[PDB]
Image (cartoon, rainbow, N blue to C red):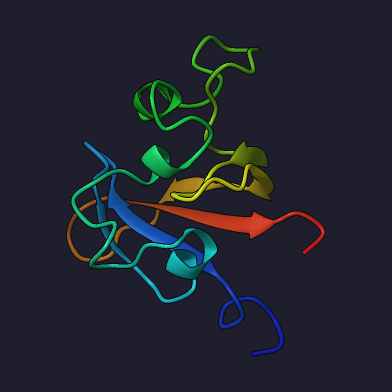
Length: 114
């Protein structure tokens, strides 16, 4: 409890095909305000930079979406928003690291200067 992996490691495990957050730990959940049983079935992006459109866009081709844009991005230090709304800038990095037998997309949110 003096680093990050146990301090407040925002770990969101999802599928790479359609996403859908499989489960989340007591750290990541703490970051926003969900949990493996409170955010499951939905998409992490729903609780990041605009829960209306941006979520459905960033979940597509990913990256800038338009290559060289700042409209919808979810794989870099961006400004996210929690269920309660905090619009706090954090670092986001999505990558397929698997977890069982399917390419599992993982996202780790790290508070800036925190």
